[PDB]
Image (tube, coloured by chain):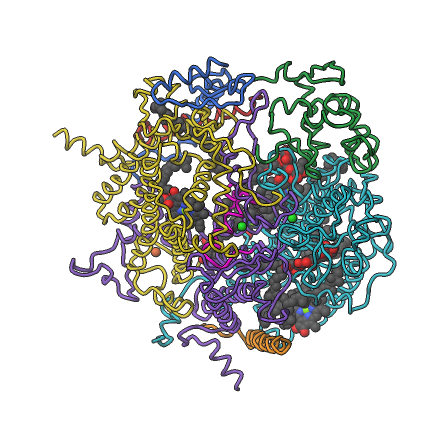
Chain colours: A purple, B blue, C red, D orange, E yellow, F cyan, G green
Amino acid sequence: NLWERFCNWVTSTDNRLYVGWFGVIMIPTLLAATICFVIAFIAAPPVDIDGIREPVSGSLLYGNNIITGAVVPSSNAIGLHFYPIWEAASLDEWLYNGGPYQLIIFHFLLGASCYMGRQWELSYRLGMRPWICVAYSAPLASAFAVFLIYPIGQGSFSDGMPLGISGTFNFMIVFQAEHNILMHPFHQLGVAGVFGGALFCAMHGSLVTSSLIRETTETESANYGYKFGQEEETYNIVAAHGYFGRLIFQYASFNNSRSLHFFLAAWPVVGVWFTALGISTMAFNLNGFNFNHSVIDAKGNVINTWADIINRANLGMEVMHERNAHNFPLDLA
Amino acid sequence: GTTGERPFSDIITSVRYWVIHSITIPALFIAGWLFVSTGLAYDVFGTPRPDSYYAQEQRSIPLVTDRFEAKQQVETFLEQL
Amino acid sequence: YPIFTVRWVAVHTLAVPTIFFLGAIAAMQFIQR
Amino acid sequence: METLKITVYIVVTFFVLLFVFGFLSGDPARNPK
Amino acid sequence: GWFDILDDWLKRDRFVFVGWSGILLFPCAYLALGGWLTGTTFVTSWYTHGLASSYLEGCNFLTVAVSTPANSMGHSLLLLWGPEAQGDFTRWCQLGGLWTFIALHGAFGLIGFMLRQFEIARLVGVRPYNAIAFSAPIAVFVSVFLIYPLGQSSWFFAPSFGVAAIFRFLLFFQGFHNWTLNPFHMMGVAGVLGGALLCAIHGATVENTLFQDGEGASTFRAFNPTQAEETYSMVTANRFWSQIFGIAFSNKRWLHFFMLFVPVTGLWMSAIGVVGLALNLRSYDFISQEIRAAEDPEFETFYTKNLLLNEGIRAWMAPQDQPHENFVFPEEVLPRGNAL
Amino acid sequence: DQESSGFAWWAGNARLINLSGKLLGAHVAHAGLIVFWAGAMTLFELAHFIPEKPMYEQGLILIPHIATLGWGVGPGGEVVDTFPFFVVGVVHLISSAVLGFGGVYHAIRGPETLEEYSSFFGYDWKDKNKMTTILGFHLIVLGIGALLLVAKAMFFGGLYDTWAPGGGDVRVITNPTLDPRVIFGYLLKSPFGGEGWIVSVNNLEDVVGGHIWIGLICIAGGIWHILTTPFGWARRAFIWSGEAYLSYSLGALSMMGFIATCFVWFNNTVYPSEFYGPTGPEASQAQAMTFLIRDQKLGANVGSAQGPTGLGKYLMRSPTGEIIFGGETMRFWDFRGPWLEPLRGPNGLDLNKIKNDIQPWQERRAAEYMTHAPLGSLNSVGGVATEINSVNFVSPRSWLATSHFVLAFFFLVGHLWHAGRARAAAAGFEKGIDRESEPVLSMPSLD
Amino acid sequence: AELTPEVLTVPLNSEGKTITLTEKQYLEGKRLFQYACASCHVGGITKTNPSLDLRTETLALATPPRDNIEGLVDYMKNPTTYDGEQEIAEVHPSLRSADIFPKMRNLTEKDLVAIAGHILVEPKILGDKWGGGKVYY
Ligand code: CLA
Ligand code: CLA
Ligand code: CLA
Ligand code: CLA
Ligand code: CLA
Ligand SMILES: CCCCCCCCCCCCCCCC(=O)OC[C@H](COP(=O)(O)OC[C@@H](O)CO)OC(=O)CCCCCCCCCCCCCCC
Ligand SMILES: CC1=C(/C=C/C(C)=C/C=C/C(C)=C/C=C/C=C(C)/C=C/C=C(C)/C=C/C2=C(C)CCCC2(C)C)C(C)(C)CCC1
Ligand SMILES: CC1=C(/C=C/C(C)=C/C=C/C(C)=C/C=C/C=C(C)/C=C/C=C(C)/C=C/C2=C(C)CCCC2(C)C)C(C)(C)CCC1
Ligand SMILES: CC1=C(/C=C/C(C)=C/C=C/C(C)=C/C=C/C=C(C)/C=C/C=C(C)/C=C/C2=C(C)CCCC2(C)C)C(C)(C)CCC1
Ligand SMILES: [Cl-]
Ligand SMILES: [Cl-]
Ligand SMILES: [Fe+3]
């Protein structure tokens, strides 16, 4: 059958890159988002992100370098409305209002969601256990948080994270002004997740490199002591555990490789999950702890803490973000 | 293997331990309490009491201005209370 | 088994003040301005 | 514009139909054991 | 000999190894940790900063800090017996003496810990790459807590030891140094986040390429630390990532060294850039952009928006974050957009 | 013990997979916990309820559900008698004891397996007939429950209707919408802005009608699954095991949880703002209204007032031309609410109605909703992050929206977890790779 | 610094008589002010109309004078515009409009003296911060 040949090739394990059914969506959507991103980063004209007819330049050809360049998010006048090309009277209007942003982020989110599914899929075709895709769900959820979830709760794709280095920082700063995310325990767990992951990654790598079993001379790389697919382990887990158990105390060390590797997966993934959830729940304006004026003296004078110093800085971001867009005294959008 | 001390399991399980420590853990805990309830923690460390941050008509913060007569500057602040 | 060891000292320099500090922090909840 | 809208709708339909019909064409059986 | 007798006792196999490095490590670490705990519970910041900062004053775990000494102390070591406290424990606390106490005993503790990793590595029989990797934490601590304030006017502008105090430090560095724009911090982000990534992805790969060595559905039991065979399949994990991502590890030794390299390299890059910020040698601007924007009021990028935010931070937080400056900004000089 | 089943203590409920009596026990025991919380939470809310305060200034999420169903409230949402709240809690609480008693009995006392005790309650996961039959029964239960809502709306007091003329009130629903072009038209609208998918349902008729429809759809499908076995294409497209079915429902419970989030965030019909506080878009629109009324009273001509950007300060147009509120609230112009629709003409906000027809109760409503926007800190300080302590408030909408996004996200993770494992258990490598038959070692090399 | 009898002494009427509130009395007004008022009046500003604050200076130039206990009680009974020309109970909570403003129903005469007492006392404690807005946060 001809459809069975197609299905046999879509699902082949002999392809240099695995395609698969998730890939039948992934490949076109990612290619579309990638091509449009490259073109808009170089060439897009200014975009009126805040919907106040004050366009924001973001591309290289319009006076940006790699650091200041962005694909600018679509207009605040658009809000959450869907805005493909065909909804616009002309390419010129589409570029002015932020069209490439929606095109890119929606194709990308679709493409990365299917990337996750592709990971389950090839793993199933290979006889593997299936949960690598669960780990990749932590950055995917984070991407979902800042491109889709946070716009939904706020009410405009214009509050999505710009596709750009400086645009990203403009997102972090305005976010802290509005939601106090440093004082939110879900971002703190994210910090604990990436710092801890960095630490543990550093740790595991130094401990295994430390226990490598002598197989080479000095005039060559220790790496040539491992050959792709040997059945013998290349380091000495017992020596590494002997070392690290003495560094702290023995029961604070791992003697089970599977138990240690599970810990390596779980610590950053969980912490990133929570920090995705922190962006996703601050989207609905459940904000970080507010301790402003929390400590008071017996007369009633405010006794500042460091929280009140954080507030003075938050205030200064607040009254300067979107400096022309507010006509009324409360920041409700 | 095992290094040689008595396992912590057998210790918090043994009756002798909790004979000793049902007195000691509460004692220190009560000790800590009294350190704050007597007001000693305020004077040992110099931390102001809720009525010792300002004088009754002052909103200026007693900031140390001089490096070397600083010890005396803090005490000139406490006197104005 | 011996009773006092290097570990013994180590657990008690952390633990004795911990319980003491928790006591002091306990009473602080009842301070009214 | 409308020609583009129809062009993309056809493209999207095509791939979505590859996906549903591909995953119905006996996926569980495609494994090594 | 007595030295060989003391060496015998220091290097005894106990529950908590001591070693020669212990004579430095334990008292300094214990005093750094004890000093932080002591101050966050009892010690104010009313005379150094105008801040409350202890459990005893009303602060919670997120707002307690051992705060930095007032700007007027300069870079004084602030020793207890030194000239500022003159042996008065009460006044030393009120002057910020716990800050240097912690930072200095902490600095020496970190030396002791790195010596500890050396000492244990030599006794046990392994290469000393764990201590090498710990250079990055030390480089970070030295640059941020010692060099950076030594570059500035005083220990005051070092980070105060506290959760929210650290957050303020982060925000000071955005408003004043535009630290996000510095490529040395960017390289640190990429080594921290790239380390998290390698940690997560290598753990998942091993757990999802295991061989079947037991019959239990919880697969942990199927490992014995004395076993000789690899517990997961490098061949299968290679094919998977080759076909998913394009490239895959094929050398287990290079893979684990790479896990050392990345986050160690990145912390060292962020230290370098902090060393630059000690001197206010910032990546604050791009000159080309400022020349365009000064001549063209319709030019607006995300770079120029961030600078408006930095200017708002500085004017709105400086009167209380830098109280030794006696700053008084009348309302009309404060930068602010419409309405807010 | 783990040596008997394979699963460890932290995965101990996986030992229940082929023990239908104990598995029934845990399930019935869990359902008691839900019903317990529902009753317990209600009485807590009632013990703390104050009638003079609005419900949303008091941290209530259940009493709002009960009042929307028409029990306890009078005109405009005012609570007139609290005894129906009391009943709902007591009855749930009393029922949970029943559900608990049976759940515990089946768990540790009843027969561990049902398959030898009775051929009707017993089930084998791989038996596609018995599974569709159990599915069918439960579909029938779901249909009945959806009709109970119809019956409460049509035959038993009605529902609270924020849109009712003269101001919202309890109202009996006489003409549910049955027109499939409306009911299934919701299922075909876009999820994006100004459309809303099913979240845009803005009248009780459409609500009551859709439930008549799924009420009938469910009972029919229930009968259909009791009478049929799965076709051949479904047989080869699915995984037939207990974990597999658990994963299918995790995905579904996830999809539903996301949908619930959007519903309570945007919709003010089945979530009456009278009870739940204004929505996000609403409070922002209410802010613009409040300042329009105030400035106009001072003598401003809100149609021709130009704002700093050049756009109108009080009034601008939408991208399709509609007269909308100006300022940054321009993003919220899809908002619809009973306090604002009187000022809506066919072209949008009617400048003449703004000038002459604003009523005091509208100015009161706009001010109330502006100063109760769903914005607050984790410790329930009300406002933007830069707000000083004073107002103890977080909108129920925030609390309900954030929790159910967390639950939804984790259940999607749950779906990915159990789905992949189900697939690997069925294929026979969920425990790792056979050394003596490694699949990759028999495929050819990529290069 | 203490909440002294000197601090808790505010004008009673407009003819110079005074009233000395207790600490308990002041704490009552602060709790009642947060229950009924803070939604619009947090910190002495006015969210729904920033042009009119709760500062003692502003209340003094109001008509009738609102910088003593009498007029604030009167205002909470029958509020008017800044020149006393329009009665505004229809849009401002009061005892007269407790039917449409329910949080004013359960307020006794003692509760109105406390709330007024808190409005006059707080600027004495916090100075320019009362009514100053986010510049003084
Ligand atoms: C994606 C976000 C992101 C990421 C990944 C990073 C990553 C990093 N930032 Mg940056 N940063 C960000 C955003 C981010 N930042 C933003 C938006 C800003 C605002 C502009 C800042 C502002 C900022 C500042 C101000 C600083 C950093 C620094 C750093 C580095 C800190 C590394 C570290 O572990 O220090 C942690 C500290 C150490 C490892 C020192 C050693 C500590 C010892 C080992 C601890 C031992 C404890 C002991 C056992 C007892 C503890 C007990 C107690 C808990 C009870 C790292 C490269 C720092 C830097 O560059 O330093 C060189 C720095 O000072 N960032
Ligand atoms: C909602 C939670 C929930 C529920 C309903 C169940 C239910 C069950 N679990 Mg699971 N389990 C859970 C959570 C839950 N588990 C969690 C969180 C963990 C991790 C710690 C485990 C770990 C776990 C393991 C490791 C095992 C089970 C097993 C079981 C089954 C037998 C338990 C047993 O032998 O108890 C014996 C215990 C007792 C007899 C003590 C008394 C327990 C009862 C229920 C107390 C009830 C109190 C209540 C107030 C009484 C109400 C009275 C009424 C009149 C109102 C049972 C069906 C077992 C199994 O599968 O066996 C084949 C098994 O091996 N569970
Ligand atoms: C969806 C559920 C839900 C929601 C939306 C609310 C919402 C609300 N509740 Mg209620 N409540 C709930 C469940 C819920 N509750 C449950 C399950 C209980 C039983 C314990 C209660 C018991 C309860 C009481 C007793 C009270 C409330 C009250 C409140 C209000 C204040 C909440 C607050 O301050 O929390 C504080 C915030 C937290 C405690 C943060 C918790 C964060 C969680 C732990 C994160 C969990 C993440 C994830 C699930 C963990 C697993 C991760 C892993 C898989 C990797 C608010 C209106 C109060 C009120 O005002 O009543 C009038 C009140 O007094 N609730
Ligand atoms: C989903 C719930 C459920 C299920 C599937 C079962 C299934 C079973 N139970 Mg169990 N049981 C349950 C709940 C359940 N029970 C509850 C809640 C209790 C506590 C009241 C008990 C108490 C109990 C006892 C004491 C015994 C069983 C036994 C049995 C077995 C024989 C039942 C029989 O022949 O009934 C035949 C049918 C009937 C008797 C008519 C039932 C009419 C129902 C109750 C009308 C109401 C229906 C309505 C939809 C309920 C709404 C509930 C609400 C929460 C929404 C069977 C395996 C027996 C057993 O296994 O002995 C070895 C046994 O001794 N059950
Ligand atoms: C809880 C509800 C439920 C469940 C779990 C099942 C489960 C099952 N049904 Mg039953 N069924 C139900 C309710 C349910 N049914 C009801 C209420 C009815 C009456 C209308 C039916 C009518 C019905 C029929 C007529 C058939 C089944 C069959 C089946 C089996 C295959 C399902 C399948 O392939 O779906 C997968 C779904 C598809 C392949 C559809 C194509 C893809 C769609 C378009 C995806 C759209 C999703 C997207 C996100 C949009 C969602 C929102 C909105 C726009 C729609 C399976 C055992 C089949 C069987 O074998 O019966 C013997 C069968 O022929 N069911
Ligand atoms: C049971 C609770 C689950 C909590 C969420 C899941 C935690 C682990 C998820 C990490 C996925 C990583 C990517 C693949 C990782 C991967 O491949 O895992 C592999 C590893 C081993 O798998 P096995 O096949 O042996 O076991 C899984 C099943 O087959 C059961 O046998 O899985 C586990 O051990 C799961 C442990 C469950 C118990 C988890 C409890 C830990 C969380 C405790 C709560 C923390 C809260 C913190 C609050 C601040
Ligand atoms: C300073 C100084 C010194 C020192 C002293 C010391 C050394 C001290 C120590 C102290 C200490 C040593 C203290 C301790 C403390 C502790 C604490 C205070 C704790 C607490 C805890 C808690 C609270 C817990 C919590 C938690 C966690 C974390 C986990 C889970 C969750 C929970 C929540 C449970 C000297 C005199 C020599 C000299 C001079 C200076
Ligand atoms: C299986 C199992 C389990 C579980 C269990 C469960 C989950 C159970 C449940 C249980 C339940 C679920 C129970 C319930 C109960 C209830 C009750 C017991 C109630 C009672 C009530 C009453 C008596 C009422 C009273 C009243 C009235 C009448 C009115 C108002 C007031 C009052 C409240 C007084 C666990 C996990 C442990 C583990 C082991 C195994
Ligand atoms: C009540 C109500 C209503 C209505 C509702 C309705 C009428 C609904 C319907 C609904 C529906 C009617 C739904 C359905 C859905 C569906 C789904 C959700 C699907 C799923 C699917 C799947 C899951 C599949 C999968 C797959 C593929 C894709 C391929 C091959 C393989 C498999 C089979 C796995 C309204 C809105 C009016 C108003 C309100 C109330
Ligand atoms: Cl901005
Ligand atoms: Cl605005
Ligand atoms: Fe490894």
Of A319 and G94, nearer the camera is A319
Q: Main secondary structure of the magenta part?
A: helix
Q: Is residue G15 left or right of residue E93?
A: right
Q: Does the rendering let one see residue D11? A: yes
Range of residues picked out in magenta? A160-187
Residue positioned 76% across, 68% down in the render: F220
Residue E278 in picture, x, y percent from top left = 34, 40
In the rendered view, would you say F373 is above or below F6? above
Q: Residue furthest left?
A: E1
In the rendered view, would you say F283 is above or below G69? below
Of G109 and A251, nearer the camera is G109
Residue positioned 77% across, 51% down in the render: F340
Indicate the quadrant where residue F395 lies: top right
Residue F250 in picture, x, y percent from top left = 60, 59
Residue positioned 86% across, 51% down in the render: F165
Q: Is residue E32 left or right of residue B36?
A: left
Residue A318 in picture, x, y percent from top left = 56, 43
Q: Is residue A179 magenta?
A: yes
Q: How many marks do you count on the picture? A: 0
Q: Is residue F408 left or right of residue E18?
A: right
